[PDB]
Image (cartoon, rainbow over the protein chains, first blue to last red):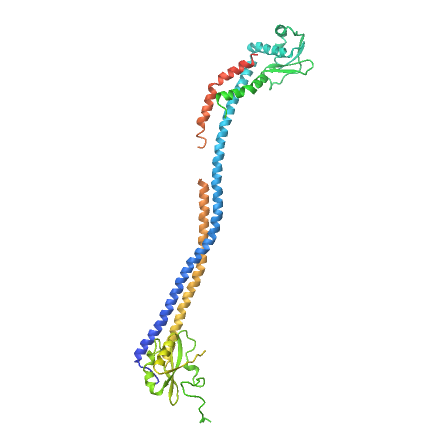
Length: 225
Length: 106
Length: 95
C-alpha cells in the first residue's frame, strides 16, 4: 500500500496538525520572550543613557544654583550696607546744613553796616593786639576800605589803651583787595616784614571754630559709634 | 551488463556499513526540528515495528516509515521525527529488540 | 508517502521563522527607540532645569525701615539747630 502506519488517514492528519501546532506555538512563545526582553532592555538602556547625561547636567546645575543664592545674599548685604551708609551720610549732611546756614548768617551780618561797623572795628583791633607792632598792613574787601578809612582814629585810639606797652604809629590800607567769593567780611592783618599774617575774616574764624566745634556738636546731638 | 553477480562484502543489516545502501532522499536535511533515524528490525518483528513505531516516542511523524533495505534476517526502515526525541525513540526501540543504526549525516 | 507530512511540517517551520523574524525586527526597533526617546528625555530635562534656574532668578521697600530714623535725625538736628547757630555766630563776632 506504500503507506506504513497503524493509524487511520484522519488520525495521521490529527497528529500532523498536532506537531505543526507544537512548532507554531514554540515559535510564538519564542517571539513573545524576544519582545518582552526587548521591552525590558529598552527601559534599562533608556534609563542608562538618560542618567549618564543627567549626571553631567545636575553637576553644573548645582554649581550655577550655588552661585545664585550667593548673588542674592550679596545683594541683601549690599542693600543693608547702603542703608547704613545713607544714615551716616544723613548725619553728616545734617551737620553740614548748620555750618552752611551759619555762614549764610555771617554773610548776612556782613551786609549790615549798622551792626557790621562795630564788629569790623572789633576784629581789626584784636588782630593788632596779636601782632603788636608800631606799623601794620590791613587787607580787606574793596567795599570795606571806605568804612575803614573813616574809622582809623577809632582803631588807633582803641588799640592805644588795651596795649599801652606797645603804641601804634601808622595803619596801612593795602591795595591788594580780598576775594569776593572767599571773604564776606573782616580783614587780614600782616606786619611790615610780611612774615606774620593774621587772617581775621569771618570765614577764617568760622573754619577755625568748625575744626573744634563740629565734633562737639556731633557728640552732643548723638553719641560716639 | 545488467545481470551482475555480486558477493557478500558485508554482514547483516544490523551491523553493516550503510554508505552503499542509503541515499540522500531517505534523510531529512536542513531542519530545526526534523531528523531521520534508521532502524534495523529482525524479520519476525516487521509487523510489530510497523504498528508500534509511531508511539515509541513523542513527536514521531505519523506514516513516515519506509523500507530502505532487506536481507535474509533483517529489514532496514527509516523514520522521521523531532530531534529532541531521538534518544527516547532509540531507547524504546532497543527495548523492543530493534537495532537502531546510528547515522549522523550532514 | 512521507512528503505529504514532511512538506507540511517544513511549511510550519517556515512560518515559524517568519514569526521569529518579525520579533527580531521589533527588537531592533526597540533598541533604536531607546536612544531616540533617551534624546527627547535628555533635551526636555535640560530645558526643565534651565527653566527652573531662570525662574529661580527672575523672581528671587528696602528704604522703608530707615526713613523713621532719618526723620528722627532731622528732628534732633532741627530742634537744637537754631541754638547752635546762635552760639556759633556770637562766638565769631565776639572776641
